[PDB]
Image: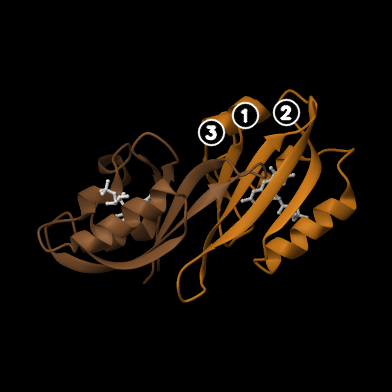
Chain colours: A orange, B brown
């Protein structure tokens, strides 16, 4: 169904966990993405304005939803319905980010 | 630093990921918690009414916070400042649960 990406909150948000659906959608195994920023999913037809909105939202730890053009490991484009939210503790500290991916290419 | 627990949405919400602080707080390594329901952290003096509120919130995929008595691997009791929220896709399907153990 829907992919899930968990990243660290700091140091440019390296991936720390992906679910099985993430591999189904993107063609990447966990081994191939752990420790990397998720921006490797982008490529030349990705909308720069959309990437800028993601960058500013993540810097502010503000939830954001975007439809963004991404690329499978072998280079096949797909439309990623992407929702990112910070994970906060009760003091308001950001512990992680969680991203949900749906392939909406259909 | 605050602990984080990620579980699957269905079956019995098995743990699929914990952060470093989870191990600092609880004394459990990832290998000894992955695939288990987090209820193993509970013990003799855990408040049953608190557990029942968590049970109903998870069943309905509702956000909840509880201060719950838990036990470290070595059996020492500690107060877990626990907050749980569902992770949803845009069609409203629950993909996972995320728990935070606030430091
Ligand atoms: C939890 C999380 C999941 C993300 N998932 C994706 C994704 O699936 N596709 C994507 O293009 N970018 C994703 N990103 C965004 C990139 O990692 C990055 O934040 C974005 O490209 C903007 O920053 P940049 O301009 O430094 O690349 C995700 C970010 C986070 C924090
Ligand atoms: C993501 C997540 C994290 C959880 N973390 C804890 C925890 O740290 N301590 C705890 O006692 N219960 C925790 N729980 C709750 C138990 O897993 C379980 O839902 C609760 O005991 C109520 O269900 P039960 O009556 O079937 O045990 C967590 C649940 C979820 C979904």
Mark 1 → mark 3, Cα distance in angstroms = 7 Å
| Coordinates of residue A99 in the picture (x, y in percent) | 62, 48
| Location of residue B82 by image quarter | bottom left
**What distance separates the C-alpha of mark 1 from that of mark 2?**
7 Å
Element type at mark 1: loop
Q: Residue at x 32, y 59 (%)?
A: B53
Give the residue pinned by disc 1.
Answer: A28
Q: Quadrant of the C terminus of chain B?
A: bottom left
Mark 1 C-beta to ligand 1 under 8 Å = no
In percent of width and height, residue A23 lies at 59, 29
Q: Residue furthest bottom?
A: A91
Determine the secondary structure under disc 3. Answer: helix
Contact? badges 1 and 2 (CB < 8 Å): yes
**Based on the displayed image, in which of its 4 quarters is residue A79 positioned?**
top right
Question: Do the residues under discs 2 and 3 have CB atoms within 8 angstroms?
Answer: no
Both marks 2 and 3 on one chain: yes
Evaluate if marks 1 and 3 touch, with contact meaning CB atoms under 8 Å apart. yes
Tag 2, which secondary structure? loop
On the same chain, marks 1 and 3? The answer is yes
- In the rendered image, the vertical position of residue B10 relative to residue A47, given as above or below: above
Left or right relative to A37: residue B74: left
> Which residue is tagged 3?
A30
Residue designated by label 2: A72
User: What subunit carries mark 3?
Assistant: A
Residue in the foreground of this view, choosing between A28 and B8: B8
């Amino acid at each position: 169904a829907s992919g899930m990406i968990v990243t660290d909150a700091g140091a440019d948000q390296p991936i720390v966990f992906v679910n099985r659906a993430f591999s189904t959608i993107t063609g990447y195994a966990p081994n191939e993405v752990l420790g990397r920023n998720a921006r490797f999913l982008q490529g030349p037809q990705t909308d720069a304005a959309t990437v800028a909105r993601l960058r500013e939202a993540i810097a502010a730890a503000r939830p954001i939803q975007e439809r963004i053009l991404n690329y499978r490991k072998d280079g096949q484009p797909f439309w990623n319905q992407l929702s990112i939210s910070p994970v906060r503790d009760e003091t308001g500290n950001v512990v992680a980010f969680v991203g949900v991916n749906t392939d909406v290419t259909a």
